Amino acid sequence: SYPQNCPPDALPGTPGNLDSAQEKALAELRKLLEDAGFIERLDDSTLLRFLRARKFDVQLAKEMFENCEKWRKDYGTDTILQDFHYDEKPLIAKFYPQYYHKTDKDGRPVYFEELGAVNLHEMNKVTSEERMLKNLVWEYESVVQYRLPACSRAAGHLVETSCTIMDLKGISISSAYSVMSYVREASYISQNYYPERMGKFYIINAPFGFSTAFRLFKPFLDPVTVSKIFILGSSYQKELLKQIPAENLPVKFGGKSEVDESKGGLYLSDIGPWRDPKYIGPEGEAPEA
Ligand SMILES: CCCCCCCC/C=C\CCCCCCCC(=O)O[C@@H](COC(=O)CCCCCCCCCCCCCCC)COP(=O)([O-])OCC[N+](C)(C)C
């Protein structure tokens, strides 16, 4: 168990903040699904996320959920946490940092990626696209099962979304052509299978003409997705501190938070309430390496 209701000042159609019509829509969809033979992921949070993804259209949300359930069983997502071994992670992480550090003002996990060293040919030597997306699915289920529950216990309310920061420092804009396929697949996964899991998505240190580049990706992205994405130049600090306390924001990004050499520095640690024994529960500590 952990807090299951969003704060009351959150949007409607989120748990704890339903009107009678949203209520009836949730009970209807739940009954449809129970009739279909489903069992897992009939909790308020999940179903309201699919409803919200379809503006509370019951038949459309049901179709969404059913396709997602189908893909979970086709991809083997339900055991992926125990059946995927991303052994090449220490290699890829040196091109492509992907880490967490603490929480935002609403309790969301803060997730970071740095793209300035990503080189496609090198990682092509290290891995395949299919495995990188297996790892993406793996990190989604991991944040769901470990990070979000602890985050919810720490905030005192439900937390179901991430605060993501993606640093473009040092990318070459001409590189974007090379990753559309990957982005198309990643976004396809995030939108159809993890709906309503984005919270805020900053893009910092963006180089000039990047707003032009991002156009190549826009035909992949839901409008709800694009409304979450906030593109910034090198003046990102004030904006980040609006959303994350300085104590929780790494020093390289304008805040005051630090990680020691001992603990693996910023990249290799995984500091946050999902590491705190006060806030870990029946799910245990997140896998860590
Ligand atoms: C060799 C093998 C294959 C090769 C693959 C190589 C590709 C690798 C390289 C780079 C990958 C870059 C894109 C990755 C997409 C990340 C999105 C994501 O996580 O999903 C988000 C959906 O959000 C979207 O759908 C929006 C994505 C658009 C922004 C990306 C364009 C910037 C690229 C600039 C171009 C620079 C080019 C660089 C060159 C100097 C969800 O966000 P969230 O909920 O906050 O996150 C969930 C948290 N979790 C995931 C931890 C669970």
Image (cartoon, helix red, strand yellow):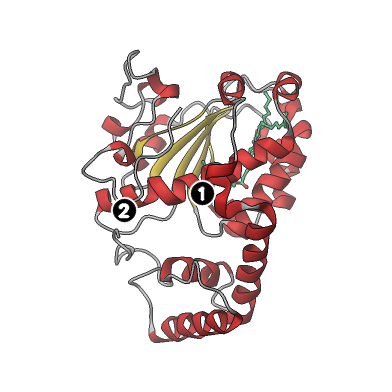
Q: Is residue 121 visible?
A: yes
Q: How many marks?
A: 2
Residue bearing the label numbered 2: 152
Mark in the foreground, 2 or 1: 1
Q: Is residue 151 left or right of residue 66?
A: left
64 is higher (above) or lower (below) than 58: above
Q: Residues within 10 Å of mark 2 (few under 14, many from 20)?
A: many
Q: Quadrant of the N terminus?
A: bottom left
In which quarter of the view is residue 259 placed? Answer: top left
Q: Give x and y (percent) for residue 202.
A: 50, 39
Q: Residue at x 50, y 67 (%)?
A: 40
Q: Give x and y (percent) for residue 194.
A: 56, 56
Looking at the rendered structure, the secondary structure element under dot 1 is helix
Q: Residue at x 38, y 77 (%)?
A: 18
Q: Which mark is residue 52?
A: none
Looking at the image, do the residues carrying marks 2 and 1 touch, with CB atoms under 8 Å apart? no
Q: Quadrant of ligand 1?
A: top right
Residue bearing the label numbered 1: 141
82 is higher (above) or lower (below) than 63: above
Q: Is residue 138 left or right of residue 271?
A: right
Q: Residues within 10 Å of mark 1 (few under 14, many from 20)?
A: some
**Along the line of sight, which residue is nearer the eye, 201 or 45?**
45
Inter-mark Cα distance, 2 to 1? 16 Å
Looking at the rendered structure, the secondary structure element under dot 2 is helix
Q: Give x and y (percent) for residue 277.
A: 23, 40
Earlier residue among tags 2 and 1: 1
**Along the line of sight, which residue is nearer the eye, 200 or 234?**
200
Q: Is residue 106 visible?
A: no
What amino acid type is highlighted by mark number 2? Ser
Q: Residue at x 62, y 65 (%)?
A: 69
What amino acid type is highlighted by mark number 1? Glu
Q: Residue at x 43, y 66 (%)?
A: 45
